Image (cartoon, rainbow over all chains, first blue to last red; front, side, top):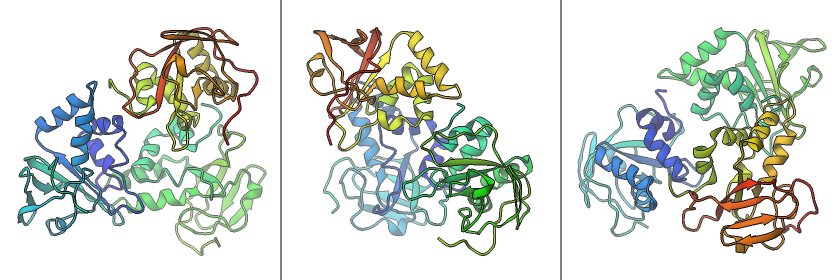
Length: 148
Length: 149
Length: 151
């Protein structure tokens, strides 16, 4: 597929292992559109270290930290471009995201220096309020003041 | 499986590739029973020509024509026999279907000359309002006056 | 997976064919948590004899007997230990389950002498009201007096 009505379809092509972890943690709903949900923005960790730690925790006898990391990577907002990375937005952790620097096709966040670039091959269908960014380096915030 | 509580289970046995496209185009709901739905009737294109065109469009940079075709093949009505192929019915394109020709076990539609025969191997559960027809030739209406809702 | 947020993940690891049948018979909801549902307790038949019989019926032209057997194996209650195998409980057949005897880690039921031991490798996520027992021998009651269901 080259156009996407669901983020899972893109993830099934880009990292089916991570999609299986998300399904195995009963988190597919976090990733999915819902009527009263502003949107979904998924932050895909480029660097294998973040993903390997998710996998190791996910398949352990306490997958609690894999769940919280995945919550920090999923925003119940539709944020397609650098312009929309403002205001009271954040992940399924309540933590508010703050922009440090913006470029034409890149955002850098405070509180972890997450370097985020839109996934070049993620194009939603025209209704769909879905976005995928690649986190090239840094970490998404785990703790901090909540957005409200 | 030989009696079916879901059309997807029948389709998985005949053309799993097509079911994957339906899933990947977020159209599994169209295919599924619902409280507010008269039923579901699925029109399976027998001719590999139609399905190959669906696959090529679905995996292209614009799957709009795959979506439109799949919508034309899914009726949110329960139409088990030729007798019930009448009235204000049609697909998720909204186009009213008009029968040209009827037989005991076949309907031929106007607006594409769709030739439809009930699938010999699809029998729903007694409490499921599901039907599957096989389109032997022609095409389901894409365009036309809408049925009333 | 070593902790389970849904029973399907556990069953996929032990008998994926059986999970596919439950999906294909539109019984995943029986196996799933729901807001006003006391819980889910799944009885896995250890003996391949019982599971092969479910498989033959499920792939037949009338899978009704596969449905009934699977309904008898799924309880819309959370019963994690022998202590909770009491009261007005039973499977989706509606048949009341009655304990004959309990041990520290086993229950033996009337009406079939079902011998049930909690699955050693099933731990729910904290606060998921899910349980899996292994039926080592006997059969879960198929017919019998109904338990009193909530409204």
